[PDB]
Length: 100
Length: 50
Length: 139
Image (tube, rainbow over the protein chains, first blue to last red):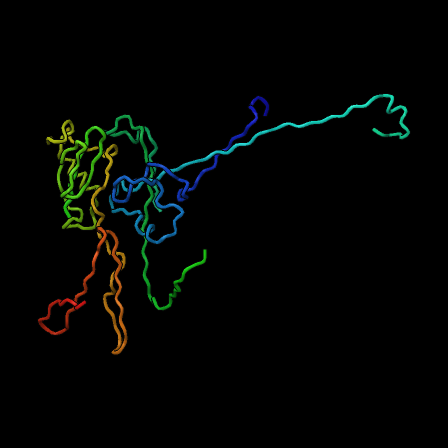
């Protein structure tokens, strides 16, 4: 719509387990703070999955935390044009009708 | 899956945090397995090309 | 393994480090506890032990002790940094019973994760005869 500049922005939402999800809200299963918010990224090693597995007892409090992240994109607009010029004597005295 | 959600406000007010600006949501479940005949499963371990 | 806890009042950080270790950041010693609980090895993790340790100490001064109303009971602000060696766990365990016939090769495999680095292994064997004790297998 008019009166909004020349650009458009949108939001993409990154999944929980993707590598792009980076933040400081992670808390490890032991309760100690951990650098990674997501449990494990796009990692298919069995060792990482085995080590970082959520675990709780019957009464559970403050064990495992996660976080989320979003990204944005953009687009823009340009303009083009061209023209041509003629004279009346050309169209009147041309041997070809319907040149226009 | 069992999910519990408590939005911030009056319900989250507590003696620790009288204002109750905070909130949380949690998920929990159980899982187990029993294997009757392990001889039926098979596996071939190998390297893979780049 | 016994663990030792340090608390920094300004940053609200509780540091768990090995018994021989020490910190020069200005924290004070709150107490000590066993990471694998002797009575309940699997029911209690580090967070519960740190909470029980910090319950006793006083809010205004981490060195001194006080009753309930002046305790350190809010663990939403408290953050825990682990500096001690990770606990040894048995990812793969030996089968309880192995059956075979004479003249066939038998293989035992065990997988251990955690600990320090130069984890070693030693295997021991006992006979079925009465009054027999574990004997080292000659490497």
